[PDB]
Image (tube, coloured by chain):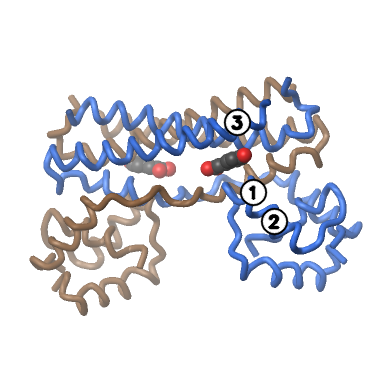
Chain colours: A blue, B brown
């Protein structure tokens, strides 16, 4: 039920058609919480069946969203990063092959960072907690910081490899 | 087939029984590439069926591992971080509820960081590319940097919330 709360959250600022929900997943929401098309309407069906939407949130849906929002949950198990599995097995690579693999990864992370920086610039063309775009600013700065940090770590490791 | 290359990689430094593979997933490998018990023996069966292991790697298994190691792959889609979905929907929280949620997350990330720091200290009790423990050092420093960066971002956001 990976889309339950994304969808309830989308409806938090008032009614939307299904096309409009589908369209929200093609924009900024789908960079960090991607949906498959085949998941969306079945989730919409379940949510309606559960009393949480009728698409507008019901009182019940608002409560369900709110309860999830404030719930403190343990940090989950680490996300499997296939690149890092390779790094774990680096003993099986020559120094030159390690360099090539890490350099390729560094290029890709820097490239992803430039795409994020373009998105940031668009968003920011005076941020505060009270801004309506604060949630968007949170997911975009989180992604910026994550990729900057990855780039920094890769540069450090390459200085050990090279 | 999420365990294919983890398992081929484990066998890269010579023969192991299944218990010994199961035991490796309970240690450091299972912090960033967790296995379910129910996945391991079925993967072992497939790998044997495919000619990649007989447990020792065959020539074929070594080549398969090597080919995967050097393959340049696109960066995958972002890992769904359920906390970040909440942050995206922060408009539905009061300033006080936002503070409580972010503070709880900050405590948990700092806690995870102390566990990682204990693991680092153990590992490091003169690191180089040539060390046999370089792969372990890579996955542990990556995890350290990732959680330090998360903590830093959380502290920044809390200074905006508070
Ligand atoms: O998590 C990511 O990789 C990307 C997040 C993102 C968030 C908002 C945007 O406007 C663009 C990308
Ligand atoms: O990715 C993680 O969260 C943890 C990784 C980790 C790697 C090596 C260790 O010795 C402990 C934790």
The residue tagged 1 is A27
Q: Earlier in the sequence, mark 1 or mark 3?
A: 1
Residue behind label 1 places its C-beta within 8 angstroms of ligand 1: yes
Q: Nearer the viewer, residue A40 or A71?
A: A40
The chain letter under disc 3 is A
The residue tagged 3 is A120
Q: Give me the residue at 75% from left, 38% from top.
A: B90
Q: Give me the residue at 44% from left, 36% from top.
A: B115
Q: Nearer the viewer, residue B105 or B161?
A: B161
Q: Nearer the viewer, residue A149 or B56?
A: A149
SS for tag 2? helix
Give the label on residue A23, or none: 2
Q: Give me the residue at 20% from left, 36% from top.
A: A99
Q: Are marks 2 and 1 in contact (CB under 8 Å)?
A: yes
SS for tag 3? helix
**Picture quadrant where residue B44 is located:** bottom left
- In the displayed orientation, state which residue is furthest to the bottom: B49
SS for tag 1? loop
Left or right of A98? Residue A39 is: right
């Amino acid at each position: 039920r990976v889309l339950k709360y994304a969808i309830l959250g989308l409806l938090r600022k008032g009614e939307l058609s299904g096309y409009d929900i589908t369209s929200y997943f093609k924009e900024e929401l789908g960079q960090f919480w991607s949906a498959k098309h085949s998941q969306i309407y079945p989730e919409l069906k379940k949510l309606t069946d559960e009393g949480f939407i009728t698409y507008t949130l019901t009182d019940s849906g608002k409560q369900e969203l709110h309860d999830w929002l404030i719930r403190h949950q343990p940090i989950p198990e680490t996300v499997k990063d296939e690149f890092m599995l390779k790094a774990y097995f680096i003993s099986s690579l020559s120094r030159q092959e390690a360099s090539d693999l890490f350099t390729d990864q560094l290029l890709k992370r820097k490239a992803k960072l430039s795409d994020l920086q373009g998105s940031y610039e668009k968003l920011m063309a005076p941020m505060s907690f009270s801004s309506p775009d604060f949630g968007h600013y949170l997911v975009l700065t989180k992604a910026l910081e994550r990729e900057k940090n990855y780039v920094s770590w890769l540069e450090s490791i390459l200085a050990m490899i090279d």
